[PDB]
Amino acid sequence: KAFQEIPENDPDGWECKEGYLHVVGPSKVEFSDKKGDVINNFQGTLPSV
RNA sequence: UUGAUGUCACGGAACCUUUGUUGUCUUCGACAUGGGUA
Image (cartoon, rainbow, N blue to C red; front, side, top):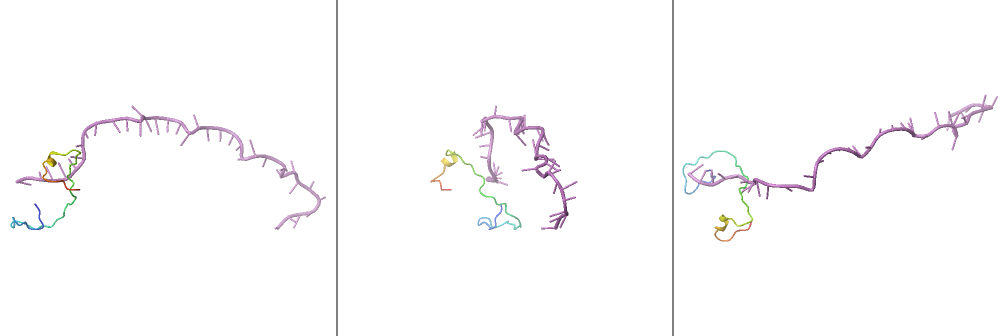
């Protein structure tokens, strides 16, 4: 894992190293015409895009 | 820019010869997506 800010529950064992961020976006997306089983188990209402 | 007693230049068809031709079924099913977990 990598965190710029130290997590509250794990404040020990973190090493600061230089590097770059490979930023692309929410690319892992599955789209379907019909409601999937995972979507059918969603609690509440589906937010807009 | 002529020369003189002598100019058929209306004396001479830019004329003659070469195929835009050749080759192609308006046809049709498997994915797309990048991690996540530890």
